[PDB]
Length: 167
Ligand SMILES: c1cnn(C2CN(c3ncnc4[nH]ccc34)C2)c1
Image (cartoon, rainbow, N blue to C red):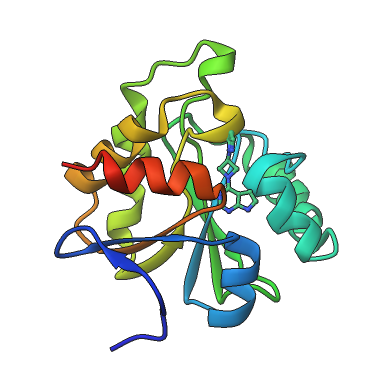
C-alpha cells in the first residue's frame, strides 16, 4: 500500500491520473519523482522548468554542479539527484527530443531507467515540448517499465484521450 490517490489503473504496475506533477509531488512526497530532463540538465521549460521552479532553483544549482563534474547525460540515460522539497530523489531521465531530430527508438532505453526504482511518480517521456506522440510514449512505458509507475498527465484533454485510446 502506498499514498498515491485517485489514479486509474492501466495495468498490473502502470497507473495514470490527470494531475500537475508538481502539485502531486508536493502532496505525496514520493521516494522518486521523474524529471523530463535534457542531457545538459538545463531545466528551462516543460516538466523540468516546472519542477525546478518549485524547488526555488535549487534543482538547477545542483544540476549545474553535476554537469560540471560529470559532463552531459546520454539521450536515453539518467542520473539520480536530490528531490529537494518535492521527493526524496529526482530521477532525471532524457527521452529523445523529436524537435531536435533525436531517434525515437531511444524512448525504450529512457523508460528502462525506471526499472531501477520500485515506485515512481513520472510524466510521459518525450511528450509535450519534446515533440513525440504521447499515445506512443504510453505504449512504450507499459511495455518497458516493470516497476510501479504513477503517471501524471497535466493536460486534462490529453488525459482523456490517453485513457480512451489505451489498448
Ligand atoms: C509538450 C506538451 N506538454 N509537455 C509535457 C509537460 N508535461 C507535464 N506533465 C505532468 N505534469 C506537468 N507539470 C508541468 C508540466 C507537466 C508533459 C510537452
